[PDB]
Amino acid sequence: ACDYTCGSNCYSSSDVSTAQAAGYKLHEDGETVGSNSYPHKYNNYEGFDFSVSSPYYEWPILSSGDVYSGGSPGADRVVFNENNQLAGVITHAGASGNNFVECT
Ligand SMILES: Nc1nc2c(ncn2[C@@H]2O[C@H](CO)[C@@H](O)[C@H]2OP(=O)(O)O)c(=O)[nH]1
């Protein structure tokens, strides 16, 4: 059930998988949505120890279960690479400024 905990939001592997597929599809087509143009490159300023190689891209994952479509992105993000491999699930929740912390 609670595979990933982002602040108080609980995500299953299915939730992450569904969000990742949607974000990768848009990346593949070269399209973006929302005021911050997702999905966009994630430079890894936080220095997370990802097991998959870059480049990384961040895409919002919504607590409601809906697939992000341009509205309010919220605090949570799924990070995937060019091979459509999951790098990690991160969040602004519990972090300072525009920084991210990993979901556990
Ligand atoms: N915090 C953070 N921001 C990143 C990173 N990669 C790209 N960004 C973008 O760098 C700027 C400063 O944080 C923002 O535009 C942010 O996009 P988001 O705000 O959409 O995440 C990253 O690794 N960490």
Image (spheres, helix red, strand yellow):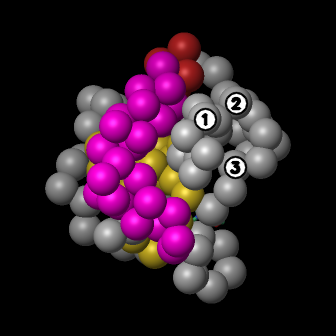
Residue drawn at 58 percent across, 74 percent down: 93
Q: Residue 85 appears in which quarter of the rendering?
A: top left
Amino acid on which the number 2 mark rests in the picture: Ser
Whole-number angstrom distance, CA of label 3 to CA of label 2: 9 Å
In the picture of the structure, the residue carrying the numbered disc 1 is: 66
79 displayed left or right of 22? left
Nearest to the eye among marks 1 and 3: give it: 1
Nearest to the eye among marks 1 and 2: give it: 1
Q: Earlier in the sequence, mark 1 or mark 3?
A: 1
Amino acid on which the number 1 mark rests in the picture: Asp
- What numbered label is drawn on residue 69? 2
Q: For disc 3, does the CB lie below 8 Å from ligand 1? A: yes
How many numbered marks, from 0 up? 3
Q: For disc 2, does the CB lie below 8 Å from ligand 1? A: no
Whole-number angstrom distance, CA of label 1 to CA of label 3: 11 Å
Whole-number angstrom distance, CA of label 1 to CA of label 2: 9 Å
Is residue 90 visible in the rendered image? The answer is no
Image position, residue 100 (x, y; %): 52, 72
- Helix, strand or loop under label 2: loop
> Where does the magenta region start and end?
1-25
